[PDB]
Image (cartoon, rainbow, N blue to C red):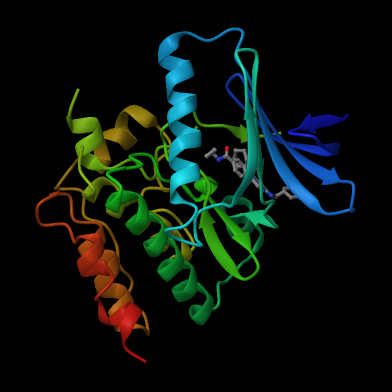
Length: 257
Ligand SMILES: O=C(NC1CC1)c1ccc(-c2cnc3c(NCC4CCOCC4)cc(NC4CCCCC4)nn23)cc1
């Protein structure tokens, strides 16, 4: 403690997560209000790294107005030495919140989906495919879920999963559909209290089972029938037959009643 951004001044409560060359702190301002300041040290970074940071602020900045399911950015500061991002602070990141709760209320799981849908929808409209969606990328604030990063800059962890990795990702060694899958696996996890491949732990065989057509996934018949359809359409292995976000936003699960 403590941090100084564009004239304003903040004291550091906790360290939420770490990069990267980056650190996220939960942060208190003068008026006892809570915030999230991400700090990037730019001393040990090449032009490829630097430019991905500049691209991140640009897009976070740009997308402010287009959806209230993108983490708010209040102000920022960039020099040749450092970057600070003053953002809204979340209650709990979806990952840890899914770990804590045993069963999820349906009306609450549908609301988080609409929310996950709107966010991802928004980035796609500005030509961004996350490519690496995980519940760690989402956050709860004032009822809603909110996307926090864009897969543009290097991912951070709390202070290395592949459950959600799409089949076409690993098969190629650029498609909106890749996000649809990962959103599916998240919805799956919220539905069947597990990711679809949680059973396996050996990577070389897990990454192999994601892509394996012979490896059939379970969809235990559940009350909400719309929901069972979304998961199926979402977790098709073939990108071109997998449901799209616009389709997914027109689906009876999100639309009926
Ligand atoms: O870097 C971020 N976005 C990129 C620039 C476009 C970013 C990172 C974290 C937050 C944020 C705000 N509040 C919380 C937040 N709030 C929960 C706290 C609250 C007090 O108890 C501990 C958790 C958690 C949390 N979890 C971690 C961050 C590091 C990587 C994995 C996920 N992130 N977070 C917002 C933006």
